[PDB]
Amino acid sequence: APDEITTAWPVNVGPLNPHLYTPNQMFAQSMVYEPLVKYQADGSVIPWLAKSWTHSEDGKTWTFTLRDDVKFSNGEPFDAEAAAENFRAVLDNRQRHAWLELANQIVDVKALSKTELQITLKSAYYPFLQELALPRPFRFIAPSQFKNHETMNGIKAPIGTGPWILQESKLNQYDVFVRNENYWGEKPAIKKITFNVIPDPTTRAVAFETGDIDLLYGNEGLLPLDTFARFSQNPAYHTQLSQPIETVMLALNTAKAPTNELAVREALNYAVNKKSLIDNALYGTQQVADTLFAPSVPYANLGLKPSQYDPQKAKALLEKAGWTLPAGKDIREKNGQPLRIELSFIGTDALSKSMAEIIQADMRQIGADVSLIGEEESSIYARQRDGRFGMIFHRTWGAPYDPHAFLSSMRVPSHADFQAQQGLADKPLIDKEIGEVLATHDETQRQALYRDILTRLHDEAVYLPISYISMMVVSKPELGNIPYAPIATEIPFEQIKPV
Ligand SMILES: O=C(O)CN(CCN(CC(=O)O)Cc1ccccc1O)Cc1ccccc1O
Ligand SMILES: [Cl-]
Ligand SMILES: [Cl-]
Ligand SMILES: [Cl-]
Ligand SMILES: [Fe+3]
View 1 (cartoon, rainbow, N blue to C red):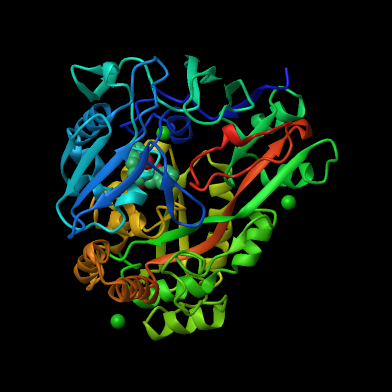
View 2: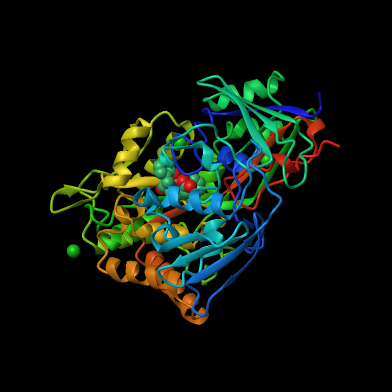
């Protein structure tokens, strides 16, 4: 059976409501549900469920011409009415989509005919098409599967137009997908995909070694990185490591002592030998990051000055700010108060703990006492939401979220980035400029605004960028080369071709 594969995920795929978040898993929502326009690696979108579109003067009114040959997996038609109903269902839950500015921008969605769909916006929102292309929430479930003409209170069957259909799910055991034999587009070569629920990274590696799974595909947490490196030399196996997809960093709390001091945040940014951190904890598998966004990120090639590892400079910065060493102690003090910073992380995540131990050791060497606070996932999520941290691990979102959607979300108070930035004197100016950059028509102004926002965030040392991380693959050689999807959160199962 070379047209059936078995893979793994730490949890079940969830209900596969196209319009909700946890516990829905994005890769799976993307397997079943499809967008009007599809994101491509080059930053553009191509026609998808919409074959063409135009906008008014006045980029506020958009009219999409939809395909007329698409059916949902249950045989019901996809048309402008079905699409319009989906937009209504999403926007009936508007507050849950605040992070995504398109959700605050849509004023009206109307089916003008079976094939003409009209969307009107508040303002001329530039990233409109890219946001329609996201895994969620703007993808389409058969409206017959709404509950009481909504999706925010749940759905019936997870019926999409996509190339995969969920066959069955068993909580804490597995999820099975089958090829859609009535897909409007190209038939996948793979007919069946089974996801075994395997929460532990070493258990996932063991399941591969035993032959129990055929494919593992994910970020730096996919499997232990020492094991991945051994696998890459094993001629019985296939492995891949993509080019970097996003940044991993610390976020520093500018509203909490002692990270409220610019000098402290600058010093911390000179204290870490990132190459050593990566060679120590990540087995050399990732790239050093010195800016929030890699220079390859749209609008982010700004020539920002890196803070290279320089513990002499880190110490001098702290000294100048009045943090000095008592005899004969290693931890600096100012006004008799110790230079102590809490780093909270998920206590069961071994990679986080490994990185945190390295960070603690590096910062001790410059006289900062980092306290490691390892907690359960729920408590960490609460800390980020509410600003109850000194430092936390954080990551960017990858294409096409970076930079515009990541920046957009910095304005949302109940999230880590706003919370980390809350202490900055220029936070209001930053949030103003983020609003402006999303709305601006003037392309030179757009570049200037991105420059200013990213330059302030960099110069104010809000983050401590660590690494640009890659997607990783481990596979049975019989599966062949495994492609990557343009959207960092999607897995392109329909492009796998064992041939
Ligand atoms: O992540 C948040 O801060 C809030 N999420 C909005 C932005 N995410 C997009 C999304 O969830 O679709 C960004 C994102 C990008 C890439 C991978 C994962 C990911 O979540 C919504 C969100 C809400 C509840 C639980 C988990 C969630 O992700
Ligand atoms: Cl989740
Ligand atoms: Cl490797
Ligand atoms: Cl001072
Ligand atoms: Fe999210």
